[PDB]
Structures are given as structure tokens and as C-alpha cells.
Length: 94
Length: 147
Image (cartoon, rainbow over all chains, first blue to last red; front, side, top):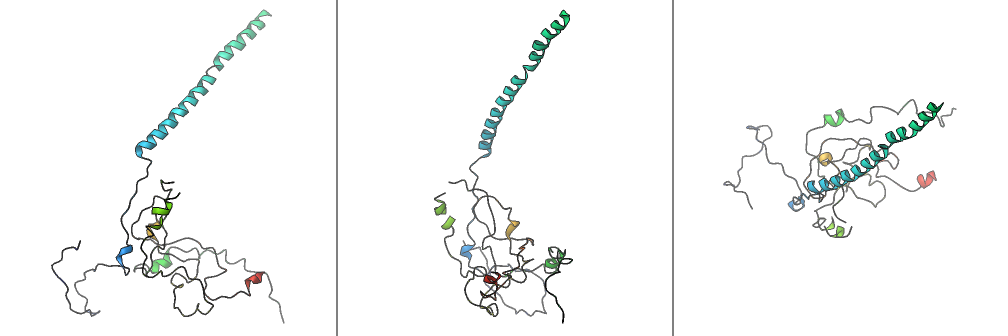
């Protein structure tokens, strides 16, 4: 698991003034690596398909209530013509 | 002689430049923040599980122990250890009202459970607190006192 590197180590001392050819070192933490713990990404069990099932069941349940309300409100036009026509005839009797 | 007992600081610190986050932290951007990581700050949303082997997968990734637990959970000595540090409580301690943790990814708090390693931004959130005020120099006469 060691990355390949031909060269071991080299040395020409670090005078703060004489910095030339500005490269950048690999910045590392001071803590032992063992707690830089492992990669884990876990799925939500509710799947893109499962939410489809749940929301479709909800849509189909709501459609029944919408149809119930429509059929409750679809009888009012029958009520108007069932209630007012006899009243119009009674007025006509005069 | 003359009185000065009990009346005024209310034209006064309802004040604006304390919530303060643009330019101060700004003026000290660019380093590398001293030895400090999570203790824990990220967040999440459920766990698609049910309460007991809760036991089993939440402490056994709290499995293998670091090498010095370092800068927030002290609790027992007397006073002027506020005053010569063996011990940390001051570079996460200088004034509370802006006081500005290390801080991984604002974490898109909250989601699921399992781990990467730590990047923050810069800072804001208001410890509106000032009265066990930050701290480490104290005794028990002056607030079993306020009682």
C-alpha cells in the first residue's frame, strides 16, 4: 500500500532568506493516522422507488376524497331544479 | 461626598459593532488552525434503524482512542489556574461574543451517519452569555451569593 517513489531523501538547509523556486510541501496533520477514520456513505433505505410508491398511494387516496366531494357537490344543480320548479308553479297558480 | 448607586447603561450597549463577523476574523485569514478537530460538530437526520444495536454501530466506531484529548472538557482545580497553563482553555477562550470554533463543512447539518475528515469556513453564532464569564478564576461566596 506504499506509493512508489524512486528517491529516499535529500538535504540543502533551510535558510529563511534564501528561499528560491517556490514549491509547496504536502501539509499533514500532527495526529496519528488511525483516527482519520474510514470512508462510509450509507443509503437512506427509503428508495427513489419507495417514495414513488408511498406518494402514489397518497395520491390515489386523495383522489377518492376528491371524487367524494365532487359527487357531494354534483347534486346541488339537481336540488335547485327540484326545489324551485314547484315554487315557480305555485307562483304561477296565482 | 456624592452617590452613584443604580441607574444607567441604556443609551448604551444595545450596541451594533459586537455581532461582528466580516472584517476582524478577515484581518486574520490565512493559516492553519492549531491542534483542534471535531470533538464533534457535524449533524444528521434519523438513522434508518430502530433503538438497540444503536448500542452496536454508535460506540464501536467510537472504537479506537486518539492520543491526547486536548482542549474542551476540563473540570477540577481552584483559581489562578486560570493563571499559568498546564492546560488549555484559552485558545478557544478570549471573550465569548465572538468566539469561533473550528468548523467542518458548516456541515450541511442534518443527514445520515458515516465519516469523512474536517474542512471549515469562518464564523458566527451568539453565546449571548456573560456571567459565569469565560472563565477559569473562581470561588462560591458571590453567587450562592446572588442568593
